[PDB]
Length: 133
Length: 133
Ligand SMILES: OC[C@H]1O[C@H](Sc2ccc(Cl)c(Cl)c2)[C@H](O)[C@@H](n2cc(-c3csc(O)n3)nn2)[C@H]1O
Ligand SMILES: OC[C@H]1O[C@H](Sc2ccc(Cl)c(Cl)c2)[C@H](O)[C@@H](n2cc(-c3csc(O)n3)nn2)[C@H]1O
Image (tube, rainbow over all chains, first blue to last red; front, side, top):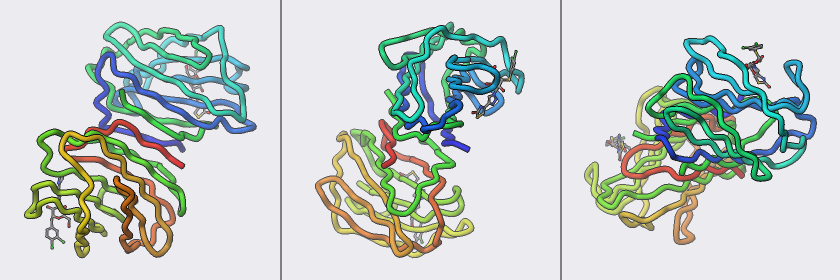
């Protein structure tokens, strides 16, 4: 599957910027952030058509392997077969996700990690760049 | 200790660009590329003053945990404190390392890996950006 990065040491307030190519026939893509694959403060899942949703962003946490309560957004600034960029940061209370087209939303920080050490990508998205603050 | 990235799927001819800030008091830094931590097609180690060398790039391979034969460059386009970007690519014959100041050198491809899946950074270099093209 997609790129996996560890040992990231992203601190509160630091921005993690990811640019990638959405596949022409994309169904969805994922960015996961947290401590490890079983402990995610953010699962970020734009669904073009996948997992029972169309053109919807679904976010969740994972704690000791258990998905939390889902959150769905009402905006979908992504298109199959294009370049897309997202930027993420956090504090003890919320993650902030910066989308294309100036849209931004918050997702609650339910793990309270001191630092985000793990990121992974998956689905129909080819990472072109990852920038750290 | 720095970022570790896996599942990179870097293919021959593709460029991996890594940009970081060299510490103001830097002794050395490392970029490791290969299959996993024990199997490196390139250990890239600019030594300001470390491991017995001054202002020298040392490169090596690692196969099943064992270091190969060292290769030393004469060029040293790095300065303590300064941002630096290094770009790496490979073919079946050699890795090519593109340095600051327009310099490039080749290092033999000793492991014949189909793809480079692993990168890690270490020492006195704070990673700012990793790009794939
Ligand atoms: O909540 C987020 C998750 O929702 C469901 S599981 C789920 C369903 C209903 C509820 Cl009420 C809950 Cl709490 C969880 C997805 O299957 C899962 N998911 C996508 C993928 C994936 C990997 S690569 C690709 O393109 N999609 N891997 N796991 C995840 O997005
Ligand atoms: O060949 C490359 C290696 O040369 C010597 S061991 C070595 C010595 C003599 C010979 Cl003949 C051989 Cl074959 C191997 C270094 O100790 C080692 N090295 C650096 C570091 C390190 C980590 S972060 C930082 O800034 N430097 N961790 N291991 C590596 O550079």
